[PDB]
Length: 293
Length: 146
Length: 146
Image (tube, rainbow over all chains, first blue to last red; front, side, top):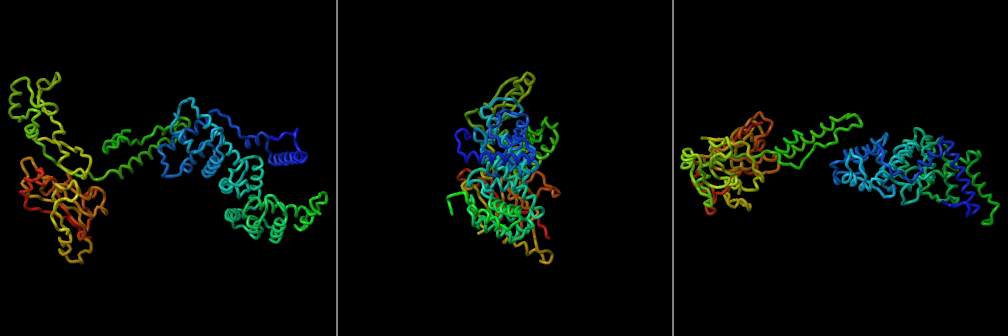
């Protein structure tokens, strides 16, 4: 959205760095640019397709006679959506529906209740007819299929995807907003999935301790086969320095962003083959500035 | 759908329909189609087992000679003795009025036939018992003695 | 108490005459030694009325058990009309899967009551002239020991 003609020098340098980082990530992931655009696209084609028509028929037949008070609409609707949209698991479809309801896809903000009412009233299966709201239905279905393309491309585990949908703050997305499938969020999700895979067999306990506010330096150090003192000192050094967002002892291992910052400190220390105090001494060498001595 | 008519008549729940049109789908060659019907019949059974309960019994005897003899006088009251034995002898006639008359048959093959008409509205059988015993009353059988 | 005879209490029963008795006064547990068996349960109950049931005319009467909680729906009561060893049912079959009415009631608890609709002659009740004749009531108890 920002124009290159009227831009600051620092903003242009930041833009160069972002473009370079995303290109390097795509090269590592064997992804074409078009695939990334599809996963990050917001405009949706408003054209009925045979797959969408089959989805509507299956959902309408399954949910007929549904009672609102007896059970939650979303939980009842999840299995048929999973069947029609080529998903491996039912709970993945449940998480996808929650995420879609938070996004409210399309030009006409669509949700499970509105979708169900439209299916109940204005839909006649087996016939091709023109309906004014039909374009919003198609856009909503297309958004659901795209969020599948997200889930399968990222490779994240089912329960961490559930956690990401339910509590974006744990993944450090802006508080009080639905999580973004923006490429900026996609790259951090891929890094999270890769870190979980690196933990190997310990991942089952680490994720459970992460979903509670339970994780500590010692358990994660045992999981990653690192020295416990190394993680403790990396956490201390991260707390001393001003990161954005700030890292505090009560979030240092509760939120994923703090863990990512601590792991970056550890990776840079092990690249230089020095302790984190070495990196702490290095970053103090801001000699080309007037802000501080 | 024949078992569903039998249900909608053993009970009176004409509104309750259980068989849905969605059992067959040509996209997938109609596979699994029977197992939806199996589920729908298991619902039709279990809702019967919950709704259906022991219906109480009565035998009431109803005498047609008293029903017509006791007929409210806004219709001409008559005992069958003095109209059977002259509507045998003469080829036409009637007594009473409305659903509670006695007359020769109307239709072209019935013109030699003698029919005696009565209405349950005049049997007034709903007055036999308190209403709170049960709101519907249904015939299980009817029988005749001559 | 449970052993009174009175007019019906409820607003539709005010023309109805009911006769209440308790199994506690039947004292049926005194009929046999205790070591024959510690529980006694009804398998059936039946009625005889030596009422002067008219020519093709018969009594309507209803009797019910006051528990109305432990026994299943519709089994709480039965109705009697031909009045002579009258189990109430059109057919009875101990081999059927359907329980009899009263089947499983213990023989020391709750109340048995017999009721007559339209007993009150001031309302010209359709049983008053017949019921005025009535002088004896017989119950036949089928109860098992186990």
